Length: 16
Length: 16
Image (cartoon, rainbow over all chains, first blue to last red):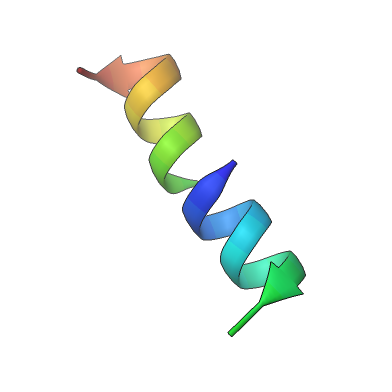
């Protein structure tokens, strides 16, 4: 979660 | 991964 990969910013799901 | 939860900083595994 949050920032990098997963649920949030960068990779996987959400933004970036 | 990275910063928040998962593999890295904050929650789950790594630091914080």
